[PDB]
Image (cartoon, rainbow, N blue to C red; front, side, top):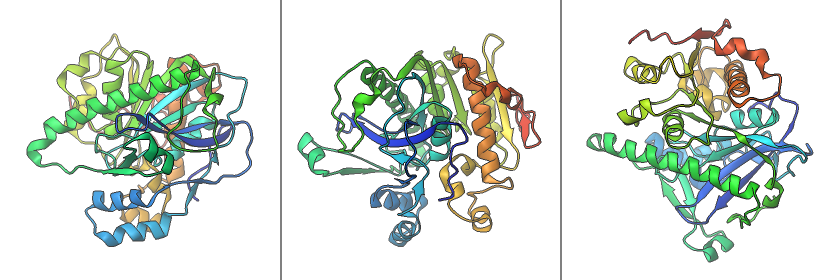
Length: 372
């Protein structure tokens, strides 16, 4: 695999958690500091139907689905599948929200890097029909047999976009808050039966969370989801929006976000109608920071930027002018510095405080889009 290993000192484990088993329950992929580092064997895209959904998302035919599966169906991401959680420390928690057409496993480069620095990361899978695909179970017996019900991305008419994208962002925010509540309840001993039968004992998570140190992060639609989530749920102490797509948000939200918020943008994705909405979040009584990564594209924040070579990836707009490892390192280091500042962590991530200010050859303070 060319998804980078995390740069921090902790070994990284990965598992999946679904509870309850229904379409209204929570589904997430967990990245976490692992006690041991025995093999990097997590499967990146774990089911054939995700490839089918990606093909529908792309507007391609039957054939693209099977082809993606042949190329990437056995690819790993560098985490220890179902490895025990590293004991004896409480970890800060990130809930992560994916973009339109994505699903929970496609931001492992970020999730694994955070976990390697001592975070637990809960990457939610949304059931708002913004994921290319997702699944749930119609009853407990279906969960026991592994009898999955698939839900695929909803395509919208233009007259639908304003109302449905706003309904979806509100559902997404609810799903982020629900995921946080599930993890906090497990932390304080709620018995949970994972609807997935996996060799990770969820009781390991009891007393494992630093409950004051919680953040929400997300890409694209997931960046709008950060803002909607912060507005509704003050258990989240700060947010980081990766190339936020601001269209889904209602006007009411802009004034209702007390928490610190960091915008990390790609150079080649942003446009004035979107940036003006980020600017609406600024106020002298609030902490808002923005940086833009030079030479990057929207896909630099997701794992398909690592899936292909330099030339095909550039042609497919999965890669920008900047090296993908260089770009994700800048985003991850700036994120860590921001998290340390606003969660009050006692780590050394303040070595990267300069990146929050845009002070790097590969960063722009603020944005290239000067509109206001």
